Image (tube, grey):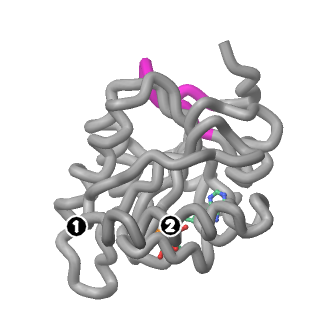
C-alpha cells in the first residue's frame, strides 16, 4: 500500500492526477517511477530533466555508465535503473519521437514495459517534446497497461481536457 492520494480513477487499473511527477515521487517514494526517456538517456527537459535535477544529476551519471556498458536503448524499449532519492527504481522508457519521424505505433510497445511492474508512477509517454497527441498517449496507456499505473500530468489545462475525454 502506497500513499498516493488525490487521484481520479480512469479504469480498474489507471489513475490520474494534476501534479508534478517529481513532487509525487518525493512524497510517495514509490517502488517505480517512469521516465519518458530518449534512447541515449540524455535527460535534458520535461520529465527526464526534472527527475534528473531532483537527483542532483545522479540519474545522469548512472545513465552514462549504463550507456557505456550497454549502448542505446531501442525506441519502445526500456531499462531499470535506480530511483535515487525519488523511488526505489526508475524505469526509463523510450516512446517514439513522432516529431522526428518515428512510428507512433511504437508507443504501444513502450507502454508494454509497464506490465513488468505491479505499481508505477508515470507520465504520458511521447506527449511532450516528442509530439504525440496527449489524448492518444492516454488511450494507448489505458488499452495497453494492465498493472496499476498512477499518471502525473503536470499541465493543468491538459489534465482538464484529458479527464473530460472518452478513453
Ligand atoms: N515534471 C513533470 N511532471 C509530470 N508531467 C510532466 C512533467 N514535465 C513534463 N510533463 C509532461 O509529461 C509528458 C511527456 O513530456 P516529455 O517529458 O517531454 O516526454 P516525451 O516522451 O514527449 O519526450 C521525451 C524527451 O523528453 C525529455 O526531453 C527526454 O530527455 C526525452 O528526450 C507531457 O505531457 C508533459 O507535459
Residue 141 position within the rendered picture, expressed as x and y whole percent measured from the top left: 36, 43
Is 144 in front, or is 116?
A: 116
Figure check: 66 above or below 17: below
- Which residue is found at the position 32% from the left and 42% from the top? 113
The residue that label 2 is drawn on is: 65
Magenta stretch bounds? 8-16
- Which residue is found at the position 72% from the left and 69% from the top? 57
SS for callout 2: helix
| Residue 69 counted in the magenta span | no
- Which residue is found at the position 37% from the left and 55% from the top? 137
- Disc 2/disc 1 C-alpha distance (Å): 29 Å
Return the disc, 2 or 1, that comes first in the chain's sequence.
Answer: 2
Q: Residues within 10 Å of mark 1 (few under 14, many from 20)?
A: many
Is 107 in front, or is 156?
A: 107
| Badge count | 2
| Residue 12 counted in the magenta span | yes
Ligand 1, what quadrant? bottom right
Mark drawn on residue 104: 1
Residue extending farthest top: 1
Amino acid at each position: 500500500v502506497n500513499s498516493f492520494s488525490g487521484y481520479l480513477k480512469l479504469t480498474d487499473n489507471v489513475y490520474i492526477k494534476n501534479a508534478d511527477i517529481v513532487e509525487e515521487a518525493k512524497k510517495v517514494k514509490p517502488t517505480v517511477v517512469v521516465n519518458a526517456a530518449n534512447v541515449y538517456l540524455k535527460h535534458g527537459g520535461g520529465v527526464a530533466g526534472a527527475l534528473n535535477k531532483a537527483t542532483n544529476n545522479a540519474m545522469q551519471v548512472e545513465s552514462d555508465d549504463y550507456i557505456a556498458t550497454n549502448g542505446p536503448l531501442k525506441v519502445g524499449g526500456s531499462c531499470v535503473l535506480s530511483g535515487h532519492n525519488l523511488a526505489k527504481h526508475c524505469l526509463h522508457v523510450v516512446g517514439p519521437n513522432v516529431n522526428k519521424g518515428e512510428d507512433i505505433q511504437l508507443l504501444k510497445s513502450a507502454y508494454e514495459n509497464f506490465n513488468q511492474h505491479e505499481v508505477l508512477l508515470a507520465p504520458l509517454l511521447s506527449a511532450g517534446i516528442f509530439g504525440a497527441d496527449p489524448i492518444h498517449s492516454l488511450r494507448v496507456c489505458v488499452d495497453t497497461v494492465r498493472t496499476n499505473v498512477y499518471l502525473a500530468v503536470f499541465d493543468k489545462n491538459l489534465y482538464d481536457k484529458l479527464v473530460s475525454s472518452f478513453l
